[PDB]
Length: 49
Length: 49
Figure 1 (cartoon, each protein chain N blue to C red):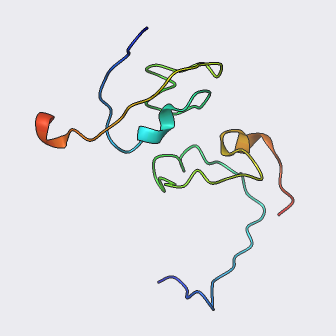
Figure 2: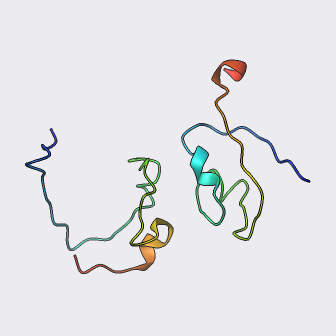
C-alpha cells in the first residue's frame, strides 16, 4: 500500500485523472493510465493560508 | 454582453490555427464533458469548420 499525499491549488483538482496532461502534472508528477487505486481530495484553505 | 437562450449567438471560425494550449489556464474550461472527441487529443484532428 502506497499513499502519496501533497497539496495543489484548487483550480485543477480533477486533472489528476490518469493519462492526462496538465501544467501541474506533466512537469511535476504524472500518473500511468493502467493505475488502480483511489483518489482523495478536499479543501484546506484555513489550515494553511 | 452575451446572448439569450432563444436568441443564442452563432459564429463560424475559419482560416486560422487551432491552438488550445493557451486555452488551458485562461478560459479555464470547468467542464470536461467532451464525448464526441477526447479533449486531450483535440490538437491532432483537423476540422473543415
